[PDB]
Amino acid sequence: ATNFFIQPITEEAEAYYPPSVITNKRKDLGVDVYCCSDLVLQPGLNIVRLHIKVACEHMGKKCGFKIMARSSMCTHERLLILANGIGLIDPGYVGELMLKIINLGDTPVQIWAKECLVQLVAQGDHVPDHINILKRNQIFPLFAPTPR
Amino acid sequence: ATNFFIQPITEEAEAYYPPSVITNKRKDLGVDVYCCSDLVLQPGLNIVRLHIKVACEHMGKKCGFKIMARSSMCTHERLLILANGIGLIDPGYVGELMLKIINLGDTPVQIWAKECLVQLVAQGDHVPDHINILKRNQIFPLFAPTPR
Amino acid sequence: ATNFFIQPITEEAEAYYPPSVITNKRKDLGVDVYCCSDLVLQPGLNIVRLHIKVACEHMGKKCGFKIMARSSMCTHERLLILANGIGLIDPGYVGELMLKIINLGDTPVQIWAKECLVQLVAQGDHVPDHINILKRNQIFPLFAPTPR
Image (cartoon, rainbow over all chains, first blue to last red; front, side, top):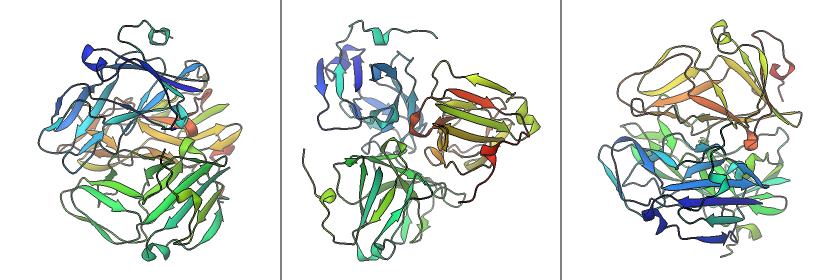
């Protein structure tokens, strides 16, 4: 099976990520993740913190996953693109998820909290089976760094 | 096996999509789709209609597919990019395919009909086996909406 | 298994690609490739030659692979993006690898040799097992063109 594990880092993110074990019944390939804070995107590159730690497992083994823009991220009011096309995250990374978002416009752009700009897709485009939202400071073995 | 199903919506698109069952002998991963109309791309975001309905099947089950730019889309004469890197389409969608194309230049850009700017790639990068072009108003069960 | 094969074309690229058979022990999905020459990226589209020939094999059969930007390519000092989101290369191509890189800034950008801007990922996001660096003018059967 293919399972995702998301743990909020800040207490602000915990309001959007309450603990549960969602079964992905409707076969949605992507896992939407929230902007847990209001943010102003200046023209050019922006580093957007997602306030979450993510691990994805395939066949009982930790695997990589992809960060992809949602159709909602780019509109006529805000020309936003992911800087690196799609973000690849290796299974060894156990830190906070960060986005590189380019504001192609010439004026600052405001994004509001609860807005989902990106989605997480597992390596090989495997549809997830469960999406576990772990509580804030649960010590999870998949989030322990393992220098190779 | 992996099979694609394309049905033109307009009669203008039918000239470019005549009915047949192509066997993908040459293992081409992508399925080119035409701009069935001349269009002017203003600077910034553009919504480009593709005048087709698409379904993709893997192992007898409906799956998702990806919209990806072709190497031909961006040239020195026209700075065009897909707005969301690559477009993900869930298997439940049975509507017309739409592109979000960003014109990064400062002057309008003209695209002519028959030009193929994007290609369709199945979930998991599975090379297709057949590419079925269904006639305009054939009622196909894979194009019937099924609210989940 | 999944194996990559890289052969430098120029003698300048050979300094960065010395011959060996690396076993991908640390399960890195991507294969970093170097800019083997200093280059100036003008605003707009740039054609960047990588001075390498690449073949990727999956289950003893030649397959396609994807060119993806690294997190290092886009920074606050240089707004660079791959023009076509991610580059798809069909298994039939046996020529030199070329990048379409868009400089979104208004002033030229300098990239230095040994800098890795992109990475190669196999079709289906299969983690490689070996990364073979073939010497400059070894005649390899996977690099012989086979018109289909």
